[PDB]
Image (tube, coloured by chain):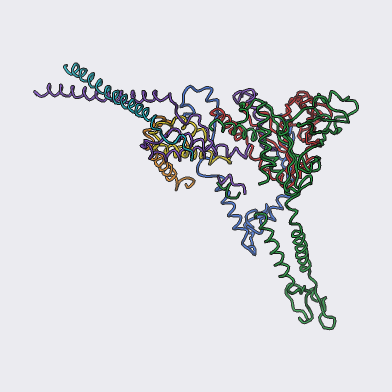
Chain colours: A purple, B blue, C green, D cyan, E yellow, F red, G orange
């Protein structure tokens, strides 16, 4: 951020010309993966900072809707969609759909069940073997 | 059998080239007479030479301060090397997610 | 609404990969000192570099009506014989020219029956394969004015309203400066009716006793009275009044005509051409 | 503010109950079944093993 | 060289610290039934480099 | 995006290893005083040191169009006989030259039919084995200007 | 002598203290099922030397 405080021509005469030469020579030597056929700054040093700011704002606003989870008169999934659209940020993989939730339910159920079974099995085995050993040793 | 650059010996190459250093020594002697006169002595000095104090004491502070700071910046306690290996070459050769860390 | 915001992201990305931000800074600085500039937006292509260009006032011509309509534009370019496309070179014999001789080309755009037409001309002959047509609302040539009057072509500037103040400030500052190089010249003055001789004061050493008196020596000086404070204060007041006119997240905190003469015309040429190129989906009819 | 999708109608409040009931009735059943099966197998294994 | 020698091992430390701080701030959202958490984590990691 | 980021990381690491940061600081100081400089990027290899180079205004020549295109570049170097590569040294007679004598080497790049051409000339002849060509947008010689006026070689 | 002698043990002590401080702050993330803790600890230790 301190490196992004500007109290334009040299981004077309020193920066873009140096990147267009090294993407040709390094590929012909086998040091870079082969790029697909046909597919600097000002908005590059902030290229990732803009994404960070948008994601942070989205998380901050999603945190504040937790008290309203027990209100029986609010359509939460559409409110979240409108809140996301009011920012302009993409909504590719930030919300779940009608499908791909029963799978989550099944995974949770299985994960609980396996551990619940194993614990009881171990405890009962230990109790039985301890009782047997004690009843065999109680005449010494 | 000592063909080029060495067809005349070691004490002969040293004597021809000895006249190229003349301006630099004179200029350094001029510089080292208002800061510390004993920093760059001549080649004809012995036990009896006396070094006189300059009328001002501003050069010594500056020279010592700069010499200290330059070495503090250049040579820290932690290592100043990296010995890195190229990327994408671990990727094309590795078969597990714990190879770069081990390297 | 979700589908309508993708199309706005595709448009801004196309203006960062094809460098649109360098010409705009140069254009915004010519508008303050002269008041005019021209902009050209070349036809988009899938996988090439097509930057945006800009023309100064000394390289184009426009004619407007009294209502404020545009009727004619003509431009001028100067290129060498080896930088030309080979198709244009095919129509000129190479023997006459040399690899370092400059040709001159012209472009003409005129209005005929609710549309626009264009062609190109070199050496008095029209180049085949350069004709075309444009709609009445998507002309890719954009003349820009800053201050608009009634019934005139071109426009006026903003620095034009404050010329007398700058001239007065320069006039005062020149004299203030030049009265300081005169007051740094040494001239002694000895008295011709006394007893001291300027020859003894010149051949002495660093510490000596010499014969003379101190009433016979004095130095010339510039005795100007209250003629320095007045000029200095007036100049300071002029500078202070000039500082208030040039402004010497926070977007809306700092802060009208340039949204009808620069911003909206660019957005209406990009959506006309990117649809035909095949980079954005076909929008519905009016909607 | 537009009130299109911010309030729930008198209808469309039945599917919410249906979904929550389904979730509870699945999770509780799975959790109850797993532990009972584990305890049942462990008891028999211990009873058979501890004899020696 | 020395342009990035003390920071050659420090850039990694700063990035890892920032990743940890941002990852510790998603714990109240653990019970939200409408959010795809792993994809959000992947995008947050991509936004740093 | 994962691969798109990996490529940038590799590009940064390569430019860090072969030191590019010393010539750049020197170049930025000549722009403020004179306004001109040149840069050259040698061909990459696998396990060798290939640093960048810089030329001052007193060692190269440029000719530009009135539109702003580049048509010709020539550079000049001074090397000693014993420091020349053996392949180049194999087209001269060693008897005429002694070690420490100096030669002048010229390089010429020009434009012909939508591409660039290259060759190297020493003494009065052309050294065999230096011919080549470059694409119109990947020429590794980059003349730099600071303030650009209209119809004028070099900047202010 | 004194190259790294007076701080000969202090250099080790500072590194160990920083390591402990960094390992202390990873306790809240011990119930997250989408994170590989063993490799994260290794990458955090290799960034200090």
Which residue appears farthest toward the front when viewing the image?
A: D10
Residue F151 seen in render: no
Q: At 63% across and 29% down in the image, what residue appears?
A: F48
Residue A32 seen in render: yes
Spot occupied by residue B67 in the image (x, y as percentages of width and height)? 59, 51
Q: Nearer the viewer, residue C108 or A55?
A: C108
Q: How many marks?
A: 0
Spot occupied by residue F19 in the image (x, y as percentages of width and height)? 63, 36
Spot occupied by residue C172 in the image (x, y as percentages of width and height)? 76, 64
Q: Nearer the viewer, residue C126 or C219?
A: C126
Which residue appears farthest toward the right when viewing the image?
A: C96
Q: At 76% across and 57% down in the image, what residue appears?
A: C163
Quarter of the figure with the N terminus of chain C: top right
Which residue appears farthest toward the left when viewing the image?
A: A139
Q: State left or right for residue F67 relative to residue F5.
A: right
Spot occupied by residue G26 in the image (x, y as percentages of width and height)? 39, 37
Give the answer, above or below, for where F118 lies relative to C60. above
Residue G9 occupies which quadrant of the picture? top left
Q: Nearer the viewer, residue C6 or F47?
A: C6
Residue F71 occupies which quadrant of the picture? top right
């Amino acid at each position: 951020v301190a490196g992004e405080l500007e109290a334009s021509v040299q981004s077309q005469e020193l920066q873009l010309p140096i990147v267009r030469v090294l993407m040709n020579q390094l590929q012909s030597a086998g040091m870079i993966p082969d790029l697909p056929k046909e597919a600097s700054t000002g908005l590059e040093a902030l290229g990732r900072g803009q994404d960070l700011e948008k994601l942070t704002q989205a998380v901050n606003m999603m945190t504040g809707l937790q008290p309203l989870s027990q209100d029986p008169d609010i359509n939460l999934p559409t409110l979240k969609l409108r809140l996301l659209n009011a920012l302009g940020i993409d909504t590719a993989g930030l919300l779940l759909t009608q499908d791909e939730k029963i799978q989550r339910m099944a995974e949770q159920s299985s994960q609980q069940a396996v551990v619940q079974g194993a614990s009881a099995a171990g405890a009962n085995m230990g109790a039985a073997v301890g009782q047997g050993a004690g009843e065999d040793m109680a005449q010494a | 059998e000592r063909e080029g650059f060495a067809a005349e010996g070691a004490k002969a190459v040293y004597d021809r080239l000895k006249n190229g250093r003349q301006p630099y020594e004179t200029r350094a002697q001029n510089c080292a007479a208002v800061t510390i006169p004993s920093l760059f002595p001549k080649e004809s000095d012995n036990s009896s030479t006396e070094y006189t104090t300059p009328w001002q004491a501003v050069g010594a502070r500056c020279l010592n301060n700069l010499a200290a700071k330059l070495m503090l910046a250049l040579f820290p306690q932690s290592p100043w090397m990296r010995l890195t290996v190229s990327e994408y070459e671990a990727k094309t050769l590795s078969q597990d997610s714990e190879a770069a860390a081990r390297v | 609404d979700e589908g309508l915001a993708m199309v706005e992201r595709v448009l801004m990305a196309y203006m960062e990969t094809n460098s649109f931000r360098v010409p705009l800074f140069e254009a915004l600085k010519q508008l303050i000192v002269s008041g005019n500039c021209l902009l050209y937006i070349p036809e988009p292509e899938q996988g090439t570099y097509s930057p945006m260009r800009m023309y100064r006032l000394v390289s184009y011509v426009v004619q407007r009506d009294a209502f404020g309509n545009i009727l004619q534009i003509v431009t001028l370019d100067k290129v060498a014989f080896s930088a030309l496309p080979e198709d244009v070179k095919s129509q000129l014999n190479a023997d006459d020219y040399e690899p370092d001789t400059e040709l001159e080309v012209y472009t003409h755009i005129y209005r005929q029956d609710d549309e626009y037409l264009r062609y190109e001309e070199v050496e008095g002959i029209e180049v085949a394969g350069t004709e075309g047509s444009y709609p009445l609302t998507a002309c890719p040539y954009i003349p820009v004015r800053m201050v608009r009057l009634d019934g005139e072509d071109y426009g006026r500037s903003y620095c034009e309203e404050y010329l007398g103040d700058l001239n007065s400030l320069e006039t005062i500052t020149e004299a203030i400066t030049k009265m300081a190089k005169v007051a740094s010249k040494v001239v002694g003055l000895v008295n011709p009716n006394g007893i001291t001789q300027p020859r003894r004061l010149n051949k002495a050493a660093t510490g000596e006793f010499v014969a003379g008196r101190v009433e016979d020596i004095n130095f010339l000086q510039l005795t100007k009275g209250q003629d320095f404070t007045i000029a200095k204060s007036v100049a300071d007041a002029i500078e202070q009044r000039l500082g208030w006119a040039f402004l010497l997240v926070a977007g809306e905190l700092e802060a009208s005509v340039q949204s009808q003469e620069l911003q909206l015309p660019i957005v209406r040429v990009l959506m006309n051409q990117l649809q035909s190129a095949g980079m954005i989906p076909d929008l519905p009819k009016e909607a």
